Length: 102
Length: 102
Ligand SMILES: [Cl-]
Image 1 (tube, each protein chain N blue to C red):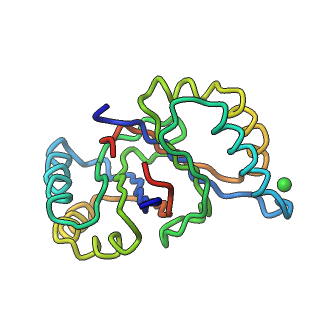
Image 2: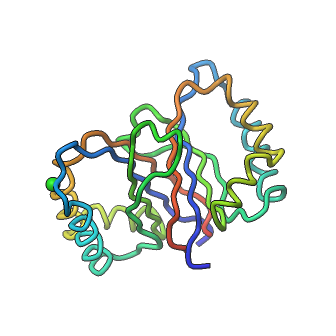
């Protein structure tokens, strides 16, 4: 298709998180492309920008379209990840939008 | 390559921006896409996320690798783009990261 839907979730976590937290997140990340439809990209990692503003990590994702991102809401890997990460997240900021493919 | 460098700049603009501001943005961006190398994606658009935190627009971009993003930072047409937009930007936050290629 000529476009895709980008969804980027920037996050600042509690200071208590450990390597274990990230190990479990990565396990949810792994389930995601297996389990959700229309997912082109799905990654969780460290923010290396200078002007990160305290947001140290992000989930970055691209879907074939906004409807695939809508369905991702009940993707069980995602419902589960959200429930897992939620209590440890201090702040988030999100960018969603349609962008050219590639 | 297996990975690409993602670069997302979220922005809120000043209340007093002029009527054709976004068209001028698009002009600088177009000139920049003509002149600067190693871009896999570059889009300036509206942020449609509910959790936008008031960051109404973003630039989203992907480069072949970190070196290509490094060359873009110093691309004269990119520098010009920043000189125009900077004074109209009220708030900015940035995500950079290496992510799986699409
Ligand atoms: Cl203006």
